[PDB]
Amino acid sequence: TGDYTDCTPLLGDRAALDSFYEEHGYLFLRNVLDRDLVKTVAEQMREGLVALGAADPHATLEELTIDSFESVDEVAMHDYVKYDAFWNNPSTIKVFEQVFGEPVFVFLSTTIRYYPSQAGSEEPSFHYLTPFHQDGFYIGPNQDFRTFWIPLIRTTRESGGVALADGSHRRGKRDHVLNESFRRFGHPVRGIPPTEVSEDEHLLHSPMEPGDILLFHAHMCHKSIPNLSKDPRLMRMSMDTRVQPAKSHRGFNAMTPWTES
Ligand SMILES: C[C@H]1CC[C@@H]2C(C(=O)O)=C[C@H]3CC(C)(C)C[C@]213
Ligand SMILES: O=C(O)CNC(=O)C(=O)O
Ligand SMILES: [Fe+3]
Ligand SMILES: [Mg+2]
Ligand SMILES: [Mg+2]
């Protein structure tokens, strides 16, 4: 469980950036998004949690917690968090265009995540997290989109985020099988057996700061890391969308907001 390689030095170099991405199936970029814009999104999520998660109205972002992710009306949270305005801000688009080397289309769907620490819990609720999977298994038909994952407040090794299997995107779609320990809508979801992820596809996770981006290939095998933070005990607050060349086919998920899919 190593660390992401910082790819920010490669942004000035089309060839070098693409070569890294091709080999590894991800890019980790530090301090490339407008931190004021990110903070505004974080504070929108915070206000949603005050209104819907019974979060402390006087807590700072890092003091924030909620009793239960599940007790929060996720549909209502989408009214609070103004992600489309963020993704489509010129400063954000510029970074996306640097990554792709061409004009882009940002998905109309974004997933917002507000996961409290469950350090010390004997029966923790982590069924709302994700098993090993590839976004391309459930998004298509085109497979040239990339997932863009951003922290809204900082993450730590203990507070979690997403773990990536380095270079796991080079053998196409992998088998996803029912996993009863991960659920959406009472339905179990499908994941890649952890045994079917090679020891050679080294698992990576680094702490990230608001302003940072993690992005990865449609066939990158990745999974949630649970929040077991204690000192500091932090929420993990993040959001993820998908982005693709403006010219590429725009599928169902690309055109359909989260609340309707
Ligand atoms: C495979 C699992 C984990 C990734 C996706 C996910 C997520 O939260 O990213 C929840 C499941 C529902 C889904 C149909 C969108 C597919 C999911
Ligand atoms: O953030 C998480 O726990 C899981 N995220 C993803 O699977 C993603 O962004 O594609
Ligand atoms: Fe995913
Ligand atoms: Mg107080
Ligand atoms: Mg392939």
Image (cartoon, rainbow, N blue to C red):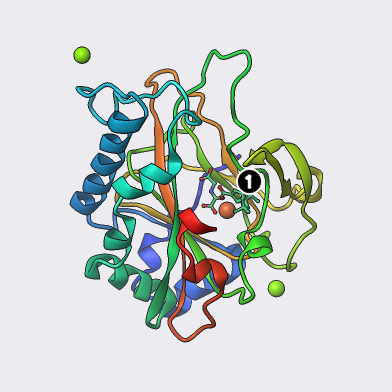
Q: What residue do we see at 24% from left, 66% from top? A: 89
Tell me, yes or no, if residue 235 can be seen here: yes
Image location (x, y in percent) of residue 181: 71, 34
Q: What residue do we see at 29% from left, 67% from top? A: 88
Check disc 1: other Cα within 10 Å, few if <14, some if 14-19, many if 20+.
many
Q: Farthest residue in the bottom direction?
A: 247
Report which quarter residue 90 is drawn in.
Answer: bottom left
Q: Quadrant of the C terminus?
A: bottom right
Report which quarter residue 168 is drawn in.
Answer: bottom right
Q: Nearer the viewer, residue 44 or 204?
A: 44
Q: In the structure shown, which secondary structural element does the residue marked by tag 1 occupy? A: strand
Q: What residue do we see at 33% from left, 23% from top? A: 54
Tell me, yes or no, if residue 113 can be seen here: no
In this rendering, would 115 be left or right of 89?
right
The residue beneath circle 1 is: 203
Q: Quadrant of the N terminus?
A: top right
Q: How many marks?
A: 1
